[PDB]
Length: 223
Image 1 (cartoon, one colour):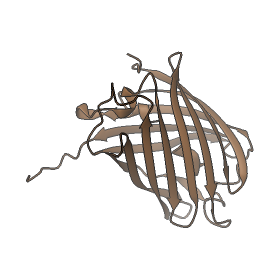
Image 2: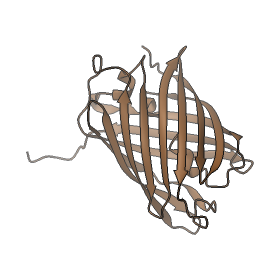
Image 3: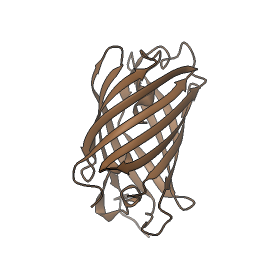
Image 4: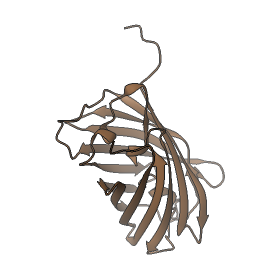
């Protein structure tokens, strides 16, 4: 098939957070049908970043979700054309980060092109002060909306001192195939655990791992 048991990826990211410009690149690999993946990330312009790398972590890969129980897989079905994602992330203490991503497949390698714009982060808040300690595991709900899918989650960012900062994610997923080799699923959920494995040099080198598994809701139904 086009999405093999093992797949590699390359990513290019550019953006600005509170008017601080940066670029990142990454390379990695994963098992798309197991829902696991690793990325080795470099900040290649604008490093060291004057803000928590964690706010970028969820912008570095939907092809690597284990879609269990035969859930129609909008992402894997989109190849060879690929798909795009876009998102607004709203932090409860003010910051808003928008992201646009193109996912393509080129000579057997997944290629990600991501652009990020973050504004209104409080200068003495935990993001700008680099007082974060990674993400809690989380659940995204995905549902069909306008010949595509949308997604929603509320995620918890760990803070120095043991607290959490919550943000809300609203995503839209659009296939580059025009619904002709694409079966779109019903409402479903993706459970994820994204972990930072290594970092060096003021977060200008970061290794990240994610496991992501899609599921219907299991619970018994009276109807």
